[PDB]
Every structure is written in C-alpha cells, then in structure tokens.
Image (spheres, coloured by chain):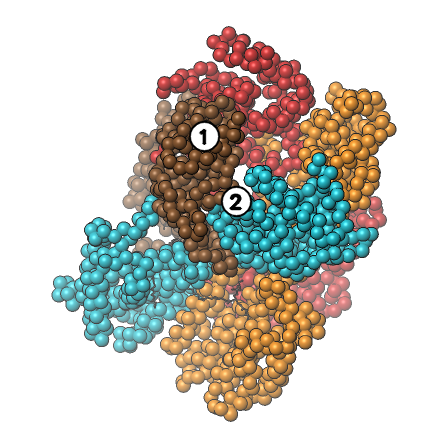
Chain colours: A cyan, B brown, C red, D orange
Amino acid sequence: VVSPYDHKYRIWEAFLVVLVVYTAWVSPFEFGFLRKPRPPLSITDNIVNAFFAIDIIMTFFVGYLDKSTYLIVDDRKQIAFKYLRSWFLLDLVSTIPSEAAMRISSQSYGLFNMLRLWRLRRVGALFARLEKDRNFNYFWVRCAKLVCVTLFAVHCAACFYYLIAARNSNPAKTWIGANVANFLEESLWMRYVTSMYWSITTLTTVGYGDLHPVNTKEMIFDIFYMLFNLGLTAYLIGNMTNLVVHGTSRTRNFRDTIQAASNFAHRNHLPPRLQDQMLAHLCLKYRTDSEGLQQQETLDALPKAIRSSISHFLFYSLMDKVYLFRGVSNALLFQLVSEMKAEYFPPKEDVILQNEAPTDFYILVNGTADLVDVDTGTESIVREVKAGDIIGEIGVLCYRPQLFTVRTKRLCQLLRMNRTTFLNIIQANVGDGTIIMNNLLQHLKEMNDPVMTNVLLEIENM
Amino acid sequence: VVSPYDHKYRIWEAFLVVLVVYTAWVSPFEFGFLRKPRPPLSITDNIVNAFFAIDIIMTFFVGYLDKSTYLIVDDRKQIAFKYLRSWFLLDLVSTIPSEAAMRISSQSYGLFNMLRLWRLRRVGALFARLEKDRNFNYFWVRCAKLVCVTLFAVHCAACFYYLIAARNSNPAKTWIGANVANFLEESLWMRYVTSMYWSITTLTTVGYGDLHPVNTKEMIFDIFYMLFNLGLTAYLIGNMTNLVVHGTSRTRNFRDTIQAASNFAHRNHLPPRLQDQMLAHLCLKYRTDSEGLQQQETLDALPKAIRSSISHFLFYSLMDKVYLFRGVSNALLFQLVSEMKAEYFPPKEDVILQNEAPTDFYILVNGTADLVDVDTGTESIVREVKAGDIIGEIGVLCYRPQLFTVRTKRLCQLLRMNRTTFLNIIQANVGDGTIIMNNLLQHLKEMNDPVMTNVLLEIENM
Amino acid sequence: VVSPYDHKYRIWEAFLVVLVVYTAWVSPFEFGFLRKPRPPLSITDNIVNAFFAIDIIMTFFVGYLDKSTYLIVDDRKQIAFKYLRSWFLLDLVSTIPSEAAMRISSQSYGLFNMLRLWRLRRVGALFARLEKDRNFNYFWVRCAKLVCVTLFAVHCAACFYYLIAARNSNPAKTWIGANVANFLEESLWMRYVTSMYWSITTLTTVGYGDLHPVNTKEMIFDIFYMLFNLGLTAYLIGNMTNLVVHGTSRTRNFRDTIQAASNFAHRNHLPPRLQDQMLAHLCLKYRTDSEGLQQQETLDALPKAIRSSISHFLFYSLMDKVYLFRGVSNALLFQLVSEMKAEYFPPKEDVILQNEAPTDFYILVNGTADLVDVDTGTESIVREVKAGDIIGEIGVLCYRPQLFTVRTKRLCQLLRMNRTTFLNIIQANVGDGTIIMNNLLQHLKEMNDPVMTNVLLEIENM
Amino acid sequence: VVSPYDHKYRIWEAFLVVLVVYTAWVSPFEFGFLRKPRPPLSITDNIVNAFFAIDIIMTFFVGYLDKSTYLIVDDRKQIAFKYLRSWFLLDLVSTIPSEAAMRISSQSYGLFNMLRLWRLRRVGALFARLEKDRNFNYFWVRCAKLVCVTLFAVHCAACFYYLIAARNSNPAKTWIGANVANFLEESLWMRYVTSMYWSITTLTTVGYGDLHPVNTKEMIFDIFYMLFNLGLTAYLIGNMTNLVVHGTSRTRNFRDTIQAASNFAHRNHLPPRLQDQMLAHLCLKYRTDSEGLQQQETLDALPKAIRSSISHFLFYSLMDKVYLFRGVSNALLFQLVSEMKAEYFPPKEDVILQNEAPTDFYILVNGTADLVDVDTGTESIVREVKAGDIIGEIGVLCYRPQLFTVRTKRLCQLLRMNRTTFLNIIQANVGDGTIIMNNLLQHLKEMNDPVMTNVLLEIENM
C-alpha cells in the first residue's frame, strides 16, 4: 500500500518525468528521421520500452486526496478502477516495441513511434503542482515552462519538416536539397542540426532566407507553422510582461509614494527635520518585509482566533512585566494581548507629541526613547524609557492632554493601544478598574516628581 | 411575429454567419484572381444571395430589446422604421447578383464583388454577443477574433498583391515573375498558395527575401502593408498580454499572500502548529471558488433583499433545529437567518479560544469540532459537538469571557453571528429575550455541570 | 489682448500645425535629397516662413492661464517677458529663410533646413492638449501620436541613408548602387520610394536582404538605426498594450463578476427565480453607463455641496408630490432630498421582503411595482403602486417589521432612505415629527382599509 | 575609518564604475580579437588593475549599515571579516594581470581576461541603488539598464562569433569568409564593425541573410544565440510595457473620471452651471500634484504624530487670527489644528448651500469668497469674506440649518471641520466651551445681522 506525501514515492515521480523528457525528444526524432530500426539507438529504445513495461507493472494503485473532506482515500479497490477508467489502453499500447509494429505493419514505424506523447500529462501536472507549490519562485517556474514548450515546438517542427524533405522523389528542389546537393549522403547529426537551425530561424522570425520552401507542400506547412509561431510569440511576450509587471510593482508603488510625499514637503516648505521624519517613516514602512509591512497586510485577513494566538505567542511575557498590569486578572491579559498593534519606528522620531489628544499609549519591545518637555522653546529631555515600559498612559486613563513628547532615539518597536478600545475592554471585567487605578496612583505617588496630576485626580473622582 | 431569444431563430443567424465566412473568403478571391464570372462559383454566389434576400425579407418581423424599459417591441410597424433607418440600403445592395453588374458595366465585376463585405457586421455582432455571454470563456473568444481578423487581412493582402502582379504588362520584373518565369501558365491553386506564402512571410516579418518588390507600385503597396502589419502585430501582442494578465491574477495574488505570510511566520519563529493553521486557513480561502471565496465577494454587492433570500434558502431548517430559538417568533427567525455569515474552516483549527472577548457564536452545518479546556497545560476535550449545534453562546448572551477552546477536526462550515449585531436584532421584537433567557437557563439545567451561571444570572436580573 | 479659449484664435493654431506637418516632411527631404534651393520648394518655404513670422509677431498679445490663480493674465508687458524667457530665440532662428543661409556659406543649406524642426513643439503641445480634452477618445489620440512619430522616424532615416549613398565617390558599391548601378539617372520619386522601402523594411524587421549595407559607414548607421528601431518597437507595443488593457477592463470585470456569481448559484442549487434575479441585478448594475453605475461611483468623490444640488435638481418636485411630506417644512425638504440614493431595479425582482428588519423605505421615480402578501404559500398581490409613491414607510416610522413584499415589474428607479439616517435628520427641525405622524395616521384612514395599526399606534401616542 | 554617505568616497565609486565600463568593452574584445598581449592595451590593463588593487586595499575600513538597528558599524575588525566572507577571492582574482597568466600558460590569455567580468557587481549594485534613489526618475534608470545589458550581450556575441570565425582552418567557407574573400588581410576595425553588424542584425531579427552560418559549430552557436535573443526581446518588451503602463495611469484614471461625470451630467440634463462646477472640481482634484491630491493621499498613511506637526507648521498662525479662538486655551488650539482637513476650491463654486444640514465649517487660507442669499429667486451678495475668516460657524455650534450660500470667486483654500469631530474635542478642555460661546455672541452682537439672530440664539441658551 503506497500513499502520497512519501519520499520513496516522489523519487519515482521525478524518475518518471525524466523518462517523459526522454520520450519528448525521442518520439519526434523517430517519427521524422528514422525508417530502419538502427539498433545503435533501437537497443536503448527497447531498454526504455522495458522500463515503461516495469513502470506499467507497478502503477496499479496509490492513494489520493478527495475534496469536501480533504482526507486521504486509500481503500485497495476504487484505487485501480478509477485509474483504469481513463487511459489504460493508451499507455498500455505505448509500450509495444517497434519490432512488433514492423512485424504487424512495415510502414507505420515512425507513425506508431509518434504515439507515446500521452506521457506529457506528467509534465503538465508537474508544472501545475509547482505553480500551486510555494517553495520555488514564480519567475523561474514560468520561465522554465516557456522554454520547455518553445524547445518542444521547435523540435517537432524540425522533425516534421525534415520528414517533408525526405519523403519526396527528386531530393533536389526540396528545401535542404536546394543548396545542399547531397544530403542523404551526409550524416544524421548534420541533418538534424540544419533542420533545427531552420526551425529556430523561422520561429524567431530572423529568416536569413537560405533554407526556404520551394514547392507547395513545404509552403503549406510553412504557412501553418508561421501562424503557430505568431501566436506562440505573442503568448511568450504576454507571459513575460505579466511576469515583469508582478515582479516590480512593490518598488514602483513605494517610489511613487516617496516621490509624492517629498514633492508635497518641498512645495509647502516644511522644515527639514519634519521632512526627513516623513521620509524615514515612509522608508521604514517598506523594507520591513514580513515584519511590519506584511504584518498588518496579512494579519488582517486572518479569522481573529489565529492572530489572537499569534499575539499571545509573541507578546505575552511583556504584559506580565509592566506595572499597570500586576494582578488584574487573567482574562484581561489575554484580551489586551489579543488587541495590540505592533509597530516599528525609525530613530529620531516623535511618536507622541505634547498636548495631543489622549488617544493611544505604547509599550516598548526594543530600542529606547526620550520624554521631551518644552518650556519656552528649549527642548529638555526628562526621562529615558527602557524596553518594557509603558508610555502615554497618563491622560489616557485620565481624560487629559499628554504631558511629554516621546522621541525614539533608536530603532524601536511599540505596541499601540487605542483609548476607546482600552476602555471597552475594561468596561468588561468590572471591578478591575479599581486595581488599574490603584497600581497607577501607587506608581504616580512614586518617582518623587512634583505631582500636580495626583492632587487633581482625587478631586476628579468625587 | 418572430421574437428574439428564440431557438428557431438563432439557427438562422448561425447559418447566416456561415455564409458570411463563405463571402469573406470568396469576394477577395474573385477580385484578385478572376475576371470571368466562372459559373462553378457563380451558382453558389446566387444561392448565398438568395439566402440573404430571404433574410432581408424575414427581418421585418423580429422584436428588439429596447432600452429604458428592457422589454421587447414587436408591433409590425416601427419595427421596420428602426430597420430602414439603420442599415437597410447597404444589405440591400450587398444582395444584388453580379450578372446584373456585368450587364451594366463590363469593368465593375471585382469592385462590386468587394462590396459584399458589408455582411461582416454579423460577425462583429456575434463576437460582441459572445463576449457578453457567460457560457463561452473569454480567452478563446478573444483568440478566435484575433485569428479571424489575422487570416482575413492575410487573405486580402495576398489577393491584392497578386492583382498588382497580374494587371501589369511585362509579366517578368513582377514579384512572382522574378523567380517563376511563367506564372500565367501555372495553376490557380499554385498561385494562391504562393501569394498566401508571401503574405504570411511578410506579416510575420520572416521575410526570406525571395518574393520581394521589384518595381515601384509593389514597393508602395508593400510599404503600406508593412505599416499595417506593424500596427496589427502590436495589437495582437496587446490583446494576448491583456488576456494573459487577467487569466493569471488570482493564482498570483494567492501566491504573494502565502509567500508574505509564511515569510512573516519564519522571522517571528512561531510554533509550527500555529504556522500550519495560518497556511491552512490561507489556502482554504483560495480553493473555495464559488462556495466561500466568491461568497463574500458577490453577496456584498447584492442589494440585501437578494442575499437575505439566498440565506433564507440555504439556512432556514437549521435555525429551527437549535434549542435557543424554539418559539420566539417567525419574524426573528428570518431576521437572524438574513444576517448569518457562512464560513469554511480547514481541519485542526481553533475557531474560538478560551478566555476570549465574547464577540461571536457559531452554528455548524457539517463537520465536527471539540471543546478544549486547559487547566495546567494539559488540555482535555470536554464535549464534541455535532453538525447542527451552537457553540460560544455562553458569554455572548451573558457578558462573560469564553469558557472553552473550540478546535475543528474536519472540513467544517460555521455561521458567525456578531454580538452587537445579535443584540441589535433582539431589541426589536422586544419582550422576546424572555424566551431566549428561558430556553437558555432551562437548557443550562439539562446537562450536569456548574450552574453558577444561573447564580450570577438571577442577581443580575433582580 | 487676444484671449485664449477663442474660436478666432484656435483656427490660427490649426493652420500652424498644418504648416508644421509640411515642414516635418520637407526639411529632411531637403537635407537628404537636394543641394540647390530649387524654387518649386523655395517659394513655398518663404511663404511658410512668412506665416511663422506673422505668428511670432502675433504672440506678443495673447493671455496665459497662470497657476495659483487660474485666471487669465493680460498685461501687455510681462506677457512678453514670459515669452522672451522661454523660446523666442529658437523660433526666431527657425523662421530665417535659407537664401540668407547660402549668403552666409555655400555649405550650410541642409544643416540649417534641419533646424526648422523646432516647430514640432506645437505638435507636442497639441497632443498634450488632446489627451487633456474629453471630446476626442484617448484610443485614437495615442494611435495618431504613434503613427506620427513612426512615419517621421522612417522618413528621416530614409533621407539620411540616401544621403550616405549619395555623398560618396564611387556611387557603385553603395547600398542603392549594389543592384541599381545607374541610380543617379533615374527619377527623384523613384529614389525616394526605394529609400522609404528600405527604411520601412528595416524598421518592421522584415529585412528582405536586398538593399543592405556594403561598406563601413552604412554599417555604422544601420547598427544605430536598428538599435533605435528596437527601442521604438518596444515603445509601440507598450503603448498599444496600455491602450488595450485599459479599454477592455470594465467588460472584463463585469464578466468575472457574472461568472463568479453564476458559479456560486450552481453549486448551492438555488431556485432559478432567485438565480435570474441575481443575474438581472448584476447585469443592470453594468449597462447603466453614466446613469446609475457612474452615479454612485462619481458622486461619492464630489464635495457634497455639489451632489446635494444635483439631488436637488433631479428630485425636488417628487418630494413635494408625496403624501407624507405635505406641509412639513422647507429646510427638512432640502435635507431629505440631499441624502437620497437613486437606484435602478430590473423587472421581476423583490426589493423589500416580508418580515424584514425595518431599515429602508423607497420612493418611485418611474416604473411600476406590486405589493405581494403571502399567508399559506399563495402570493396575492394587494396594491400596485404608481410612479411617484412611497413604499416601506409602515414599520420604519414605526418600529415593526415589514408588512408586504415589493416586486418591481418594470425597469424602476427607487430612492432609498436609511432608517438611522432618516431619524438623524428629523431630530433637527423638531416638531416636524408631529406633522409626519399626523399625515401618517391620517393616511391610514384614507381608503377605509381594514386597519390593524391605526388604533395600535394612537394608543402609543395617547 | 571611512564612512559611506560621504563625498570623498562616492567619487571613488563613480570612478570605479567608469573603469568597469572600460573592462566590459575590453575583455571580450581581447578574448575574441586578440592573441598577443599588444601593449597599447596592456599598459591600460595594468593601470586599471592597479586602481582595483588600490580599491581592494581601501575597502577594509569602510562602514556598513547593519539591519535590525539601521546604524553604521565601524570597528576595524569584523568589518574585514564580512568582506573576506563575501567576495574577497573573486575581486582578488579579477585584479591579477595577464603577464602572469602567459607566464603560466601561453594559450590562456583571453580565457583569463574573461574572468575580469566579476567587476560588474559594481554596476548591478549601482542600478539597485539608483532605483532605490528618488532623485533620478525611474523611467530613464530602467531604460539605461536595458541598453547596457543589450549592448553588452551584442558585444559578447559579436566577439564569440568572430572567435568561431577565426579559430578555424580554411578561413573561406566561414561566415565572414563566405562573402569577404580575405578577411584576415583587412583592418581590425573593419572586422569588429562587421561582427557587430552581424550581431545587431541577428538580435533585432532583421536578418538580411548575408552573413549567415555555413558550418555546424556556427549553426549551434547561432541556435543558442537566437534563443537568447528571443528571451531578451520578450524581456525588453515586458519592461517597456511595465514602464508605459505605470507612466500613464494617473492621466488615464483622471480622463475616465471626467468622461464618466460628463456623461452622467449629459444624460440627466443638468443645468450647465452645475455641470461645469462638477467638471471644475474634478479637474482641480487632479492638477494639485503634491498640494491637495497627494496631500490626503500621503498624510493618510502617516502615523498621525507626524501630520499633526505638519498641520501645526502650516496652520497655526491662522488659528490665533480668528475671533472665535481669542483666549480659549493652548492645548485646545493644538488639538483643533491637528484635525483640520485643508482643501482647494476652483473659482465660482458654492461650498456651503443654504438650508444644509449643519455639519461643517471652513476657514480661509487664501483666496476670496462671497455669501449668497436668496429671497424669492433673486440672489445677490451679502458679505465678502477675506483670507483668514471663518464661515459656517453659525448653526454648527448651534443645531440649526445654515443661513447663507458661500460661493468662491478665486482659487481658494478652506479648512473643513466636522461637527461631531468638533464637539468631541470641546468636550475635552471643559469650560472652554464657555469662552467659545462668549466670543461668538460678542461677535454676533457686534456684526449686525440685525436683531433676530442674537435674540433667538439666546432663547436656546437660557
């Protein structure tokens, strides 16, 4: 019994697609270039016939994945009936050797050799898989699919066109017979290289003009091949345009955003400190790829029982190490952890201005900042904060404008919390506002500062 | 009076467009290769003209979808006024046979045969109709339109360039007279194949170099035809590029989403159960085409009197089979059914965590989940729920944090109901939360558990 | 002062761009094909120089629309300062006749004739203006710009390459002397046609291979011209791709929406009346181009002082001619008019379901609809409403759920008013709720209906 | 220690990329066209190798910007470990002169010279830098990168194909020996020009047909080179298409908006004053490039501690120069300044209608507007307001419909302020509402709208 997702089974898959690439080269070559068996190739041909014999002896069962349950179905019957519904005679007769066919019909040599190209469904499913896969980048996958179909079309056309040249009385006034007088006397590698040269030169529309059609059957095949090439080249340029437009869109929108904001700052004559705070923020929003750019861009599309657990993994020790949440509850901790906004901040940037409306408070993870107070125009720092300290809580828990300006003097990470979101959580778990006010004003009674807020809040209650 | 949207009438339209394809090949061929009528085509010309005369009779009773009413005007007068004011004269004069034209003037055979190309308006209307259809895929419709206009332009150019070769004294020092010494003695099929070969080799810009202009009239025509081909080839690449970019947008955005989120999970070093819950949800959000991905993309655009009846069709027996809604009303059932959000979930995923904020409850359709409680790290299941049961209703009807973690274990389907949305509904039908509390607390006393929720319930009531 | 936006002045501009097209042909032809003045062109050159001297006089009194005021500046000095600082010297030296140039030196004929290509700034400004216009579609504007730059590049390269063939001792063993040895005896039109034929054949990359370079200077020019052609062809395909991708996007997204919703309805097995109600609404949302589709899509971006007066112009007679607003106010009329949502509806579609939540009510503009009441599965129509009547108000002015079901039976236009939006307006102009209730309960006892609310709300009032 | 962001060091970078452009031309030319050392290039080779040896010495002490801190590491050890672990061996071996190679082996001259192309990492990093830079436009950066890779690939193929021509017995029956009889007896410049002509003619797919392959090794190289040119040509067209679609998107969406609004206004038969108010506003919403269009397009994405200071810089003198804010507070001024939405208005446009809902009020920055009042259909101005004065405050501070209609008459700039946003600020700073009412009614009593405003307004108050 063999199930998928098996590392003994994917070896078998990759070995089969290598044999498919073998057949993709060989079957047109036998169709267009060979009448006789020529055992220097035909021995290897019968050998890979034996490989496909042991292949079809092995292939009778493997489990699959059904939809609407997404479970693995392996039950030792229906596992071979389903596989023998569709193509069993095809790859069955695909293994009959050429000696058998010449014993049957000694004119359908290459005609029966051509039949083996059902095997290319493996390559099709492989490319569908790799597009569905997330390990290999989309660029090289689409590029490889294009080069495979291009080389296959070139090879098939060179084989068919040499077939048209050979299967003709009067070898002169054929397309190879027009300039090369005696090509049946020259080698097989030479004739294949000349036919592939013709096919490449025709497909890419270079067309030097040696090796051109002379009679009518060559003209008809060349008309349909050039219509095919026109469609194929349009398909290639379309895929390459898609592939470039996807690949350079993020940098494009980033540059347009930067250009618009810097153009705004110049026509309004902003101070340059404000100007490069703007550009520092808008630059750091970009190159935090999969830290803070993809964070709010992908965590939004999660069903909120997942990103609550993501927030519980990344930030839960930090909410046990802040003074305002000492012994409040355990339900309140998970709920406050579940609704933070982890944000980055480049160095030398104010994150709370003085006399703001009270709306947010922040909790550091890393980096440092300074509390900056102004008196009559001179900026004086007050107190540097450390990674793990809450800032902005004075006035948000109250209803007062903010007291100090907070400038991140290094690269930092803060956790924003909106005020009405903070209150709507602590309107629930009633009686826990008491412990929040208690471990606030027992922290405000500390620090030995000239407490004007402490005397104002006690009258503010009653 | 024949109506449109009719199965007897569409067959007549399709037979007409088959005759239009006939005329599109034959008329440039007559203009380029023929002087006589040559009755082996004149008979078929008069047959096709007879069918077009039958259709120009038949069109006097066929209704039309008029705008501003979107009804069908079918009244045997003003249904001919619209026809005679639009294009009656041109498909009148397209129907006239050519023996009358040679009876008038023995010069205007080809110039009158070229006038039958007014019939291509049917092809244009057909392609517009097929692009407006939802049955035939847009890809091959655009591909068919491009190949038809390409083949028609190649055919017209081949016939015109052969005409420039023909109506010229000294057949030598023409383009076919340059290499083929005696082309007037060789057959008509040979000359048509050679002109198609020239026109293809020029349009695809292969240009082998034989069959080139040698005098000035051929150079002028070839200049204008190469300019037309430049515009046409750019048009084909533009259409194929559009057709590729629209075809591979969904897979592209899905892959970018998966890449960004898996890139997020690696830098933050999440536990792998969390990591493949994330990837399982983001994968299942894709391949629910026309069940869940198209659901909240198309239902939101509907004017809410439609999606309410869609929700009434799919999920109305289910809300009669839950304990919490027994005999409340019939108005409340329709209102709650109207505002459920059906969502899919891959197996092995938490959908409600323990100690969450009480915001949602869910109703199964299919699949099962498990209530999971943690005490000291060890997590045991409590009560597996069945398809058709409600989870999360405790604490939403109350105001308490959630009690158990709900982990799915099959491909489930849940119906989310928001809390404030739920309370805004039961304020209407006021006095019918009495039955809700009644069949809650009577249900809470059915199973054996701590019924301390009834203790906090009654002190909260009175 | 001659103003812009002037019909006496635009005709002068159009005549000037006709003269610029003349110069763009003639100046490279004189540079490459001529040495003498040759009066059949010299007369016309001096005429065109006279017209450009007339315009370089006329440009001293013509107003300009400056920025930061968007007002026409007309001052007769500083209207010449702006002109002299911009391009007065270059179109001065473009205007000088060439007989003075041969008076200076008998070598600088063509090199001075090429300097007249400064006049193409008029063409550039013209194409910028026509892109900023809304009367000429963007498609053919971009197409005309592309064919102009392409024809001009072809023409200049043909002239330069004939010049390289001409200015050469041993005229044989040049590119034109390779096949036509006596090319200096054959006509000027013939040599211009063969040069244009070469130049088209190189630019399209057809490249027949006759008329190819034979010495080193021709090879160097041909390398640079083919690099230019590579860039130019990529530019042309890029413009045509932009022009196709924009032009086929609305139909594309409409088709994708139809495909997704019809796919959704199939796998959920909805009843077909529901299914074609969905398709009728989704179709009618599309083909109301600039009636209802562009209405919500463009009125949203307006600053709400404009669309209020748009709503006031379209629908103000209707709110006077409805019974519920008889003698209410005039401020409340303007405010309710300003916040309606005019919406179209296809025939055979329910717009309000029975037992809905009371959220909206509607007012007909045109079209007809029917009330539908059901009790035991039988749909009985109650009362057809006429174009200009309000439906849905019984329950929104009250708080009860809806009482009937309204199916549109023609192409209708309704005006939606949301309930919470309706109540926020009637708080202002207080006391007008009394007259709304008054002409509501006065309206219940109008037809002497078997009422079941007329006493049920007067007990709520009294 | 040397730092980046330094003008002594960037000049060294530019001089190195000049020497890289030198080596990119010279190394394939030596590989293809030279066997000898030939001191007229060998001297310059040793000079350029000396400069790269100076740079590989100099690079041990130059600071780098590490991630996760965005600071400059400068420590004189581990700043060399990073350099030794990245690419030290490759630009070591690129520096070695070729006389050492001919001391080793007198056949490995060009085979060693081709290894000097490791220096192109300088060019690649330069293009990455210039795309990330915001001073040079993205258009010509991508265009220059494309022409550099195109000319380099052409140059390499020309050198390799001449190498296949040269290293061959029987110089006749090569590709250059086919038409040129004795190419070894002709100049070096001639052979380089002919090889470059072949390589351009093959890459652009013109392909005249002279200079075509005649033996098998040339056919194999030409097959791989035409496949490469197919890939590169699709890549160039894709890049130019990306570049054009991004370059003309703003004008495209603007034109589509203008088209939809003008088409809406025509099918609904609006009065033309309303119609060109619509088009005036929608035009002005475009050509405020980085004044009003990019203003709310970029300030929205800012973390609101930045744009609060932007609003504080641009608009803070104005809030001290308005009568309603005389001595109110100092925190309230910063909060009100922080939440103003500045807009532009084209001339002759109503910005507030009479009998609107009281929702907004506006403060002029620059420009003049008028007040328009209707009596029975005749409208005239009442009072012109000048830049710096507030309009619409009467009735927003109250709860009354508006009193006048405010029409602009120049390019104006107003500051919108929402009513509920205004009240949610003045609920904070309590007691400052008293001074707002006080300096309103002292302004209302002074400004003689004669009696009925001050009297009826005080009836609401007391």
- Tell me what residue is drawn at x 73 percent, y 48 percent: A403
Q: Position of residue C86 (x, y in %)?
A: 76, 55
Describe the element under mark 2 as helix, strand or loop. helix
Depth check: A35 or D209 in front? A35
- Tell me what residue is drawn at x 54 percent, y 70 percent: D151
Depth check: B70 or B145 in front? B70
The chain letter for the residue carrying disc 1 is B
Q: Position of residue D171 (x, y in %)?
A: 43, 83
Residue A90 in the image: above or below residue D383: below
Q: Quadrant of the C terminus of chain D?
A: top right
Depth check: C6 or A16 in front? A16
Neighbor class of circle 2 (other Cα within 10 Å; few <14, some 14-19, many 20+) is some
Residue A335 in the image: above or below residue B197: above
Q: Position of residue D239 (x, y in %)?
A: 53, 59
From where the camera sits, is residue C364 visible? no
Q: Position of residue A144 (x, y in %)?
A: 40, 63
The chain letter for the residue carrying disc 2 is A
| Dot 2 amino acid type | Ala
Q: Identify residue for label 2.
A: A331
Image quadrant where residue C117 sits? bottom right
- CA separation, marks 1 and 2? 29 Å
Q: Identify residue for label 1.
A: B336
Q: Is residue D436 left or right of residue A303?
A: right
